[PDB]
Image (cartoon, coloured by chain):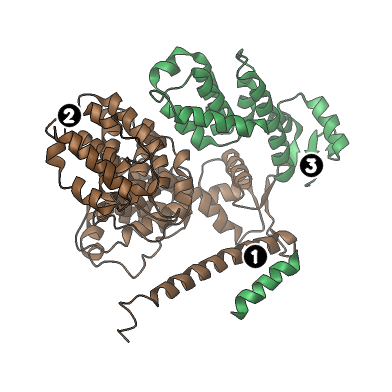
Amino acid sequence: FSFKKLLDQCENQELEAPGGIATPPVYGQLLALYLLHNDMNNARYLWKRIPPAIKSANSELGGIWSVGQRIWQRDFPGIYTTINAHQWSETVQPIMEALRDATRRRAFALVSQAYTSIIADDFAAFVGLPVEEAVKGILEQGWQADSTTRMVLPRKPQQLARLTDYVAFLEN
Amino acid sequence: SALEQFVNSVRQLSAQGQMTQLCELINKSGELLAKNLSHLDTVLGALDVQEHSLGVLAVLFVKFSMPSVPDFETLFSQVQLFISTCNGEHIRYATDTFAGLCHQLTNALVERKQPLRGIGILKQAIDKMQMNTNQLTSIHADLCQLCLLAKCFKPALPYLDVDMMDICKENGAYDAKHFLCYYYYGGMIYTGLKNFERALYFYEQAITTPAMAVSHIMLESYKKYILVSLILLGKVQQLPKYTSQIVGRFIKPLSNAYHELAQVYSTNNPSELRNLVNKHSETFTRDNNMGLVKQCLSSLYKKNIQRLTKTFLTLSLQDMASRVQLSGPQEAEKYVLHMIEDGEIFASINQKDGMVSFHDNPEKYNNPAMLHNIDQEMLKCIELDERLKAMDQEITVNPQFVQKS
């Protein structure tokens, strides 16, 4: 819930500026939070708004834009391998873990909603975790597995005041 | 010399209470204040920004109206302070000077490098001159222009989602160049956020202005309309009948490439479209609308699957891949996954035998959520009816009326 007010205050700090350029931490936090909320258009426009000097000065923005492009292309293993390839600063650390587990939950929801029979390897690639613990876990939540063929088969998951207002409006 | 008498007269005329004399004397004495260039002490003086808003407004407008202003930062800070700590209601008399000052300010911000710095300032002016939040004004066009050129779309959303009823005449300074531009930059800002319905609505509203001539932005608005209509629908939406005859004779034959795009798109053939868009790349790149035409190319693969939904209960990936011609069963799974993720289709992938199954059971229309949606639609129709009734009641009282019948 603090992410919403953080976004509000960061956007306010970006809107008012001596020359329209805020601190690099502000850019990093704003772009990371835009990636967290799955709002790609605003994140891309913010990235294009960044002046070349400040974005070239720090490779943190470059890496976060790389993971943003990975999100754009919807390559989930790319998401899980890019997010753990660089060592990140403190100001952006406690938001990317939320990004990671939110994307994990979204991937689980997508698999449960769309796929009816998925090979265990592809499901493990989507989740980003080894096959064994994912298989046991989905066994507990209630997804039937299949050995030998190694297949996963997930299962899909006051009035009267309004009425008198309506009658009063219609009676004219 | 005359500055002392001018400021004193402003003092007693503002203290007396009656207002229009100030506005009619300031607008006809600009020559007096434009031949000093040393009235920086007169800008502040004893003129507080609260009570003497019009006096300093005229001074700032005159100071900022001269070409090639030497000092930008000082005037920027002065106008920022004036807008932030303004009066609120006294500005509503000299609306023309306010609009001119804001237009000059937007030009001076955009002229060097940066439109962004003024954005907030403009969003502070909007609320201090318009009578109601649903009241279109010329400054909205400047706000949209600065927003589009600053590549920060979000801050302009609150001033665009709300509908605009009635337009301020602002002493006969609101010509068509401030109304056609606003509804076109609105289409620009919405087409970049993938909200195609409202972008199409704004483009259509911009098309049907009454105009016995051909303008520049009208052609671009028509081109982006013909692109967006193909993007969202599968066909060109017919223009409303209340359109000027100029569009049916001049603008239509001028834009032939886009009509050819529409004609080819109507055949649902994803092969000839690539050749057509490759051949006519020069004009599209010149118009600088690249990105809204590749979306048209990608729309065929999203529409053919929806068309197949109406016929096939289930399919093998190979057959449907050959039908839609994306050259590979593997990419068919990717497209189906994207479609089901974005919610345009209700499909299921079954990889044990190469299956795409089409579950056409989206809703039963018996949950309380549907009742809540119906209630929400009712509370908007009721507001619309109330607004029309209020407008009719206002019309039935005008002394110009009652005598025509």
Bin the neighbour count of mark 2 within 10 Å (Cα to Cα): few under 14, some 14-19, many 20 and up. few
* Amino acid type, label 1: Ile
**Residue B14 tag number:** none
Disc number lying in front (1 or 3): 1
Tell me if I can see residue B103 in this picture.
Answer: no
Q: Is label 3 in a helix, a strand or a loop?
A: loop
* Amino acid type, label 2: Ser
Q: Residue most toward the bottom?
A: B405
The colour with which the image depicts chain B is brown
Residue at x-position 20% and y-position 24%: B70
Apparent side of residue B348 relative to residue B82 in the rendered image (left or right): right
Tell me if I can see residue B120 in this picture.
Answer: yes
Disc number lying in front (3 or 2): 2
Image quarter of residue B364: bottom right
Residue identifier under label 2: B68
Image quarter of residue B74: top left
The chain letter corresponding to green is A
Are labels 3 and 2 on one chain?
A: no
Q: How far across and down, in percent of the image, does residue B337 sit?
A: 62, 43
Residue identifier under label 1: B374
* Amino acid type, label 3: Pro
Quote the CA–CA distance across marks 1 and 3.
Answer: 34 Å
Residue identifier under label 3: A154
Vertical placement of B195 versus B310: above or below?
above
